[PDB]
Length: 358
Ligand SMILES: CO[C@H](c1c(NC(=O)Nc2cnc(-n3nccn3)c(Cl)c2)cnc2cc(Cl)nn12)[C@@H](C)OC
Image 1: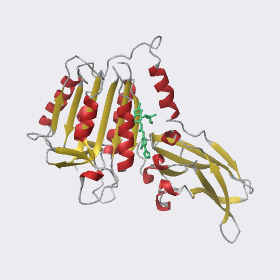
Image 2 (image 1 turned 90 degrees about the horizontal axis):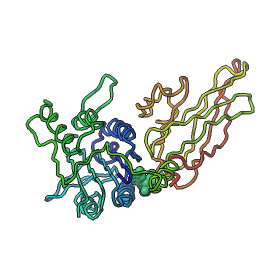
Image 3 (image 1 turned 120 degrees about the horizontal axis):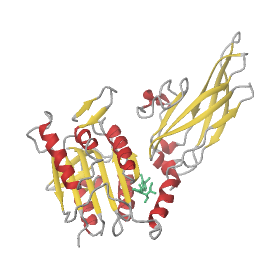
Image 4 (image 1 turned 60 degrees about the horizontal axis):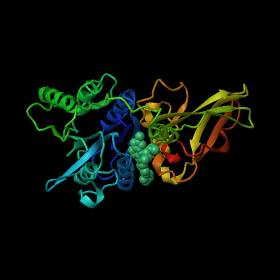
């Protein structure tokens, strides 16, 4: 492999269509599995049409001679007269092609590349380019785990075979057999595999030497800067209360913010630091921010990974941020024998985190 580059899109929260649950776990777990295989992974949740189109265009552009690419989409799919389409979260009801991404157009652009390997996997709820196309239609079918999280049928079987040092086409055929044995998808057309692979190529194949090929190092630096998290900060308030702001990442466009009281003077009986007044573009609803647990924000991956007794806020639209992430830390405090709640607030700039750097 000249390089190993992957783009994973998972669409769950649809405006005019039924919401999905499985993409979250699927995208997250496939990201980890591909990271283990030395892929530079971009993982994005809930993308609009324009966001999808730009992400796909940028991923396609990386597909230079000998590069190993992998594109995964989990979400609603649409079929109209032999063509399949990927449905963005902002798509109107009923479905219409102009609002969707045509799969056949992507395949056509992939066909022009001189990639060492190009794996295009769809997990939808309805000279050679070495393209392996997997098209799963059992996505809303999912299984509930002992964790309480929803895992997709396709991903359940894919997770178990991805790390195998075997030709990708052989790997995917075993996944199709597993689904065929699975009682939910038994005698049904759940996975279609299309392949134009003339060479024994696997996702486990090594990346070309950095002592002569510097494009992997350049793309590694460019990937790294798109995954930068703000360093944790401490804010001091006039009353004497010291607050810590902590940051965790779930996906390339999803960040969890948490606040905790590091010092509370004896005179203050009860205090809480609430993060508010986020940029409009991010579309955060205050009724889904400052939660007592990360689970209540929709963050189930990174859960006992975070400090206890904090307030948690999930920023899942970082790709929409077109300025610095400037928000307010509002402190609400109470003196034991005093009338009510005293409020104090200070603005914070955490720059352009993660995908917002690009
Ligand atoms: C070329 O850039 C890299 C890249 C991708 N680029 C994007 O996703 N671009 C993107 C552009 N615009 C938007 N968008 N925001 C608002 C409106 N449109 C969005 Cl959601 C995404 C996609 N796939 C991979 C895989 C690897 Cl490795 N890198 N890579 C990387 C450095 O990106 C992290």
